[PDB]
Image (cartoon, rainbow over all chains, first blue to last red; front, side, top):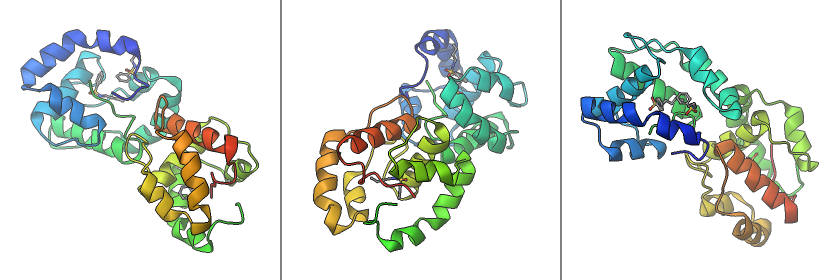
Amino acid sequence: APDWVPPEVFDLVAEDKARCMSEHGTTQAQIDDVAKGNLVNEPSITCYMYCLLEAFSLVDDEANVDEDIMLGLLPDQLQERAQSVMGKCLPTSGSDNCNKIYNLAKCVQESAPDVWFVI
Amino acid sequence: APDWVPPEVFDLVAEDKARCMSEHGTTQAQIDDVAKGNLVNEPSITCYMYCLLEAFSLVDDEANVDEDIMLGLLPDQLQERAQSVMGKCLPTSGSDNCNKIYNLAKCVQESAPDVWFVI
Ligand SMILES: CCCCNS(=O)(=O)c1ccccc1
Ligand SMILES: CCCCNS(=O)(=O)c1ccccc1
Ligand SMILES: CCCCNS(=O)(=O)c1ccccc1
C-alpha cells in the first residue's frame, strides 16, 4: 500500500497471499484497513500477517522474527528507519503467534506507521 | 529559528522534540541547517520533521498534511502567506512518509523558505 513498497513483492507474494487468506478467512478489506492505521487484533488479519511472514521465512514456528533478513529485504531508506524501530520492537512477545505479530505491528506503527505494510 | 515563530512554540514542542530527536538520531546541527536553506534528504532529519508534525496531528499515518491544523498552529501574521504556499505544495506526494515531508519542505522553501521552520 505505501508507495515505497517494491513492485516485485506484489508478484512475489501472490501465491502465498492466496494460500494465507484462504487458511485464515482473511478479506481484502482487512488488509486495506492496515495502511490507514486501522490494524485490529483479529486472527483473520493478525494470523494472515504471520502466515505471509512464514512464507518468506521471516518467522519460525514460535513467531521469532529473522531481523537480519527482514531488514535486508527493505529498501535502503526503509531499512535505515526500520533498524531503530526493530531494535525497539524485537524480539517479539505475546500469548500466541498471531498476537506476537499484532504486538510487533502495533509497536512499529507507533513510530513508523508506513514501515509496517500489508498486502 | 525565523523571528516570527511564537515563543510558546519552543516550549509547546520541547517534549516531542527530545523524543523525536532520540527516535531518529537527529542532531541539533541538522535542525539549525534548515533555516539556512540546507535540507538534505536524510531520514535523521526528514523523519524528525515527520515525527514532530505527527506529534501535533499536523500529518496523518500517510504523511498527508491537515491544512487547517497547520494554519491553526501558525500565527496571524503568517496565515495569508502559509495558505498560498500550501495551495501550491499540497497534497503531499512521495515514496514514504519521510520523503513526503522532504518534498513538502523543498516545495515550500522554493517560494517561502522562512515559512518552513524547524525547531
Ligand atoms: C521481493 C524482494 C523485495 C522485498 N522487499 S519488501 O520491502 O517488500 C519486504 C517484504 C517483507 C518483509 C520485509 C521487506
Ligand atoms: C516490514 C514488514 C512488513 C510485514 N508485513 S506482512 O507481514 O503483512 C508481509 C508483507 C509482505 C510480505 C511478507 C509479509
Ligand atoms: C510549515 C511548518 C514547519 C514544520 N516543521 S517541523 O516539522 O520541524 C515542525 C516544527 C514545529 C512544530 C511542528 C513541526
